[PDB]
Amino acid sequence: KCNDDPEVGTHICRGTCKPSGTLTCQGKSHPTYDCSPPVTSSTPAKLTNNDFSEGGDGGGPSECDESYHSNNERIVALSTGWYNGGSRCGKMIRITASNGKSVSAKVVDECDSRHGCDKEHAGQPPCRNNIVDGSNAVWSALGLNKNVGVVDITWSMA
Ligand SMILES: [Cl-]
């Protein structure tokens, strides 16, 4: 249902790193961020699905190596804050899902939480601030159906 996003810090539904601002999309204001929550040994996050390939929705090549990737690679993009100007590029993280399954994946790109809602991004909103955007291989390795679109995970460097 419709609830407050705790990363945004609204409290409109109460009792019933902060956003940098907003970008307005399909009549909806999306928060922008230059930051993400603290990276820990067990960093809570949302896993979404991204097409990293030449024939895909992901826009340009991946930031880290300026290349496209097969979606059978275990690879992720990270929200701007976590991407941190490329400091985690080429490194492995370990993702753990709610079913207790785990997978390692290589950071190859940024899930950009500063920009969006325009022609360069196809009218897609800016990324949220707590996102690990994984390939199909990441999803199937955790035993998850990418059709649910988003799941809770934790991650850390590996
Ligand atoms: Cl720690």
Image (cartoon, rainbow, N blue to C red):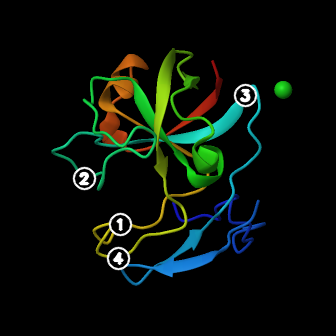
Secondary structure of the residue carrying tag 3 is loop
Whichever of labels 1 and 3 marks the residue nearer the N terminus, that label is: 3
Q: Given this view, does label 4 or label 1 mark the residue nearer the observer?
A: 4
Name the quadrant of the C terminus. top right
To which quarter of the image does residue 154 belong? Answer: top right
Q: Quick check: 138 left or right of 29?
A: left
Identify residue type, mark 3: Ser
Q: Given this view, does label 4 or label 3 mark the residue nearer the observer?
A: 4
Q: Where is 152 relative to 130, above or below?
A: above
Whichever of labels 2 and 1 marks the residue nearer the N terminus, that label is: 2
Secondary structure of the residue carrying tag 1 is loop
Pointer 4: what residue? 118
Identify residue type, mark 2: Asp
Whichever of labels 3 and 2 marks the residue nearer the N terminus, that label is: 3
Pointer 2: what residue? 57
Judged from this view, the residue extending furthest toward the left is 55
To which quarter of the image does residue 88 belong? Answer: top right
Respond yes or no on whether mark 4 lies under 8 Å from ligand 1.
no
Spatial CA distance of label 3 from label 2 is 30 Å
The label shown at residue 124 is: 1
**Observer-nearest residue: 2 or 136?**
136
